[PDB]
Image (cartoon, rainbow, N blue to C red; front, side):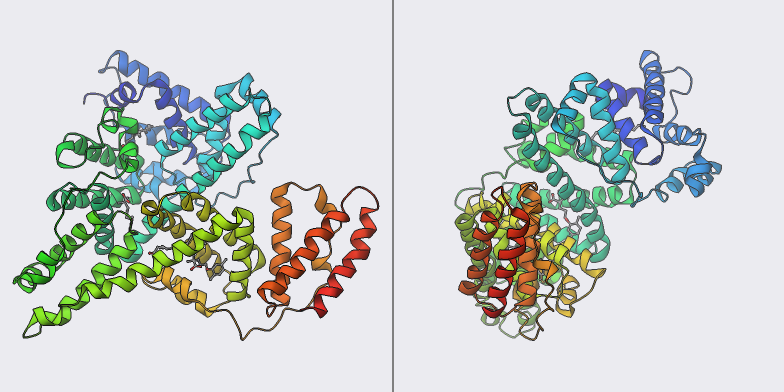
Length: 581
Ligand SMILES: Cc1ccc(C)c(OCCCC(C)(C)C(=O)O)c1
Ligand SMILES: Cc1ccc(C)c(OCCCC(C)(C)C(=O)O)c1
Ligand SMILES: CCCCCCCCCCCCCC(=O)O
Ligand SMILES: CCCCCCCCCCCCCC(=O)O
């Protein structure tokens, strides 16, 4: 209205406003120390409060984009520190705003953030809670300058909950450390998913995006009508396109506007939105993105009527193909919330191929008559992969599951580096955890969401140490072919066992006192190495060498002459194994 800064202040509230302003500057002034940022926040906050007191006070009618840039431009070492960024200040708005968007830093070469000791954290949290929370807010934002600010704030609030609860329990570290572990992983996945969505919008184009969204929205809002779903999809395409361009306030406005539309139209969308639609602006859109699926309408027709039997299949289709294809997607997805989106895209692509062929025939009905038979194999390939894999995760536990993967994937592509093999296999294990805990109906969606980041991370690592043609092929396959391509790779039978290195298999009882995390990685590294030298070992025959180590490392670790037990029985464990494999 009259004062944008006043409006935002009154809507977010002071606490939220302060945290968001800190995030906003942190992501642009990535090198300025925490103290300089607290300074800007307080200066910006004092000015806001003057505009809340009196909306027509001086400078209160300036745009928030204008006020943000001005404040960026008053930083004294701007030219010194950020170089080219300072030349943005020589421009008029809106070219100045656009100039700042281009000069952030994806890789600020800052040191790794080190998790202090539990008691060092709980005493810092008790002493100056705000200073403690906000510094960590600063450190994350400057390292993820593209992370959507409100989402980062919601994480911060969770961090607060964990420290509040655990810094008072008997075993602090037992309470706090799994929580820190979950939050970090979930924040890393959210960050990768955000950048991957924008990368996918450019790589694959707007058609692919609309197809994906139709399917997803139809699963979540099965009672909505096609036209309403398609109207939602049109807007979300704008929103994602704006957000990916990078301007935080424009992204926030577009998201907030969509949430308002949806909340003013719950009757046409979903019966599960009531609670989200009571929450304050800051949380509404995030709440909606996570709402559970509506119950689908009872007693829906077979898709056969409108898509196989009807006389006007080919006539309906040729009039507007993507509309007709999107109605198919809509009708299939609403009945199938248990499917992955990509599966639904494979079915729609199958239907599209058949109509392209058969609508040219003299008797289209005769040609496309058996099109639904073509769906059965596509549906069962990923259901079988889920059922089977999730049986093993229920049958081994995370760690042993992880070990089974290491063997499988090293045997498949034994040229991949050991750290990549280890990182990715461990992550795949964690996909098991997040997803096999869900009932059938939620399995394929869960696996799809997390696989997409895990497999992407594997591909990104792979572009930079390319050892395998077959891996490269799957990383540059189509959207729908990527995961099936991975699943299809055969064991490398034409491989050459890796040269033996005595040191690689040598443990120096360093092992008995390491964190369990490190003990796992070390065991897992060697397991990979084991398989890299002896690729031809058999299931039951490997379990042999593995169970030698099982007992070995246990007896040479019980306090005593550790040092030479790992020197003696070790050369004894190496030698027995080479001849046995
Ligand atoms: C092919 C492609 C290209 C670009 C993007 C962003 C894609 O993801 C769709 C966004 C998913 C959405 C709509 C946010 C949801 O699940 O609610 C897919
Ligand atoms: C660590 C690594 C190295 C090399 C490859 C090829 C990997 O592929 C993982 C495919 C995962 C999936 C889709 C669940 C499957 O097994 O079918 C993994
Ligand atoms: C310098 C002022 C920067 C202020 C940025 C904070 C406003 C962004 C949050 C808007 C609330 C969330 C909207 C939404 O995503 O639904
Ligand atoms: C290795 C553990 C990962 C979790 C269990 C395997 C999941 C199989 C994936 C099936 C669905 C993938 C999505 C798709 O391509 O349709």
